[PDB]
Image (cartoon, rainbow, N blue to C red):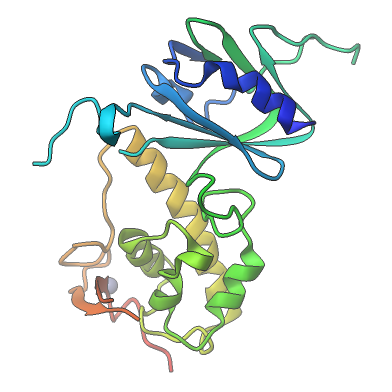
Length: 255
Ligand SMILES: [Zn+2]
């Protein structure tokens, strides 16, 4: 799979609106891409990055209230991954293969075969740091987590947990039932693995909930009482300070 050819195929569609979508991969719900423009396409290290959005002059969206910057889709091509332009592949005597995704433009369409398709932060950040990307360097992440500093400070480090902000920090911390100020050296590997997995789970879940616009129920973020019902405490901590919520009863400090 030479991704240079794939990029050459994708290039004529850059700047064109997406009319409709098809395929059998509905995990990302590609119908979000309707009436959006393929604003950019780039290739870096066995991955293909496509950007969809509505950017007008000066970088402003179409309709503005004072009162986004586009979505990035990552395509990780395996040994037999491929993309087609205005044509569909046929089987080689093993029924025709079904494309994972088909994007329709007025000029033509693109079909992607045998590839992993997931949202990502984009090319600007290294995929190893990206928490959304499947190619997430969990070795690097745990090496960062085992440091002396409290877990909130390490989690907010974009070099190793890129894309992780305040809300994900608080929710992932409550889900593992660990205190925000607990040290990464003074935590069990069980809790560390649970936290690291909850990162990847809650990130993609929250992203999918936010894209579809469905109302999201916050567990501990800006909540007066925890799910169990204990009063929630609020204070500011940082390595630059940020607002934090935690339940001391649910999340002991644990020396
Ligand atoms: Zn509680």
